[PDB]
Amino acid sequence: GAMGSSTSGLKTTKIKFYYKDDIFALMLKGDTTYKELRSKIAPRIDTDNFKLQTKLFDGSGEEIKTDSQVSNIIQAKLKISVHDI
């Protein structure tokens, strides 16, 4: 353990997405990007056009749309919400 980084952001981040009434979970090793997540949810959505946000509590939050928003939901483990678009 501990060797210059050793999983800087703890281990894989567990992020539960909320596509419609169904929900799943993704494990980001820290490199997951916004486009990588897009190809990781597309098949878990059943569509190629969807939107991801920082599932807060009322409905959704920051609409993840950049490798930083995802790596942020990765360092903060934010529930993600998926909508069909």
Image (spheres, rainbow, N blue to C red):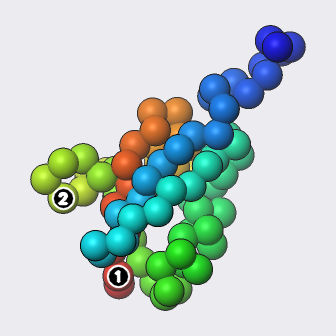
> For this rendering, which residue is in front, 81 or 72?
81
> For this rendering, which residue is in front, 24 or 33?
24
Q: Quadrant of residue 34?
A: bottom right
> Residue 7 vs residue 37: left or right?
right
Q: In the picture shown, does residue 72 fall above or below 65?
A: above
Q: How many marks?
A: 2
Question: How crowded is the residue under tag 2: few (<14 C-alpha within 10 Å), some, or many (20+)?
Answer: few
Q: Residue at x 39, y 55 (%)?
A: 80
Coordinates of residue 42 in the picture (x, y in percent): 55, 78
Locate the N terminus by quadrant: top right
> Residue 76 vs residue 61: left or right?
right
Q: What amino acid is found at the position of numbered circle 2 in the picture?
A: Gly
Coordinates of residue 81 in the picture (x, y in percent): 34, 61
Identify the mark at residue 3; answer none if there is no mark.
none
Residue 32 in view: yes
Coordinates of residue 9 in the picture (x, y in percent): 63, 28
Identify the mark at residue 84; answer none if there is no mark.
1
Query: Which residue is farthest left?
Result: 58
Q: What amino acid is found at the position of numbered circle 1 in the picture?
A: Asp
Mark found first going from the N terminus, 1 or 2: 2
Q: In the picture shown, does residue 10 fall above or below 18?
A: above
Q: Which residue is mark 2?
A: 59
Q: Residue at x 46, y 38 (%)?
A: 77
Secondary structure beneath dot 1 equals strand
Query: Which residue is farthest bottom?
Result: 47
Coordinates of residue 4 in the picture (x, y in percent): 83, 15
Locate the C terminus by quadrant: bottom left
Q: Residue at x 63, y 26 (%)?
A: 10
Q: Residue at x 58, y 80 (%)?
A: 43
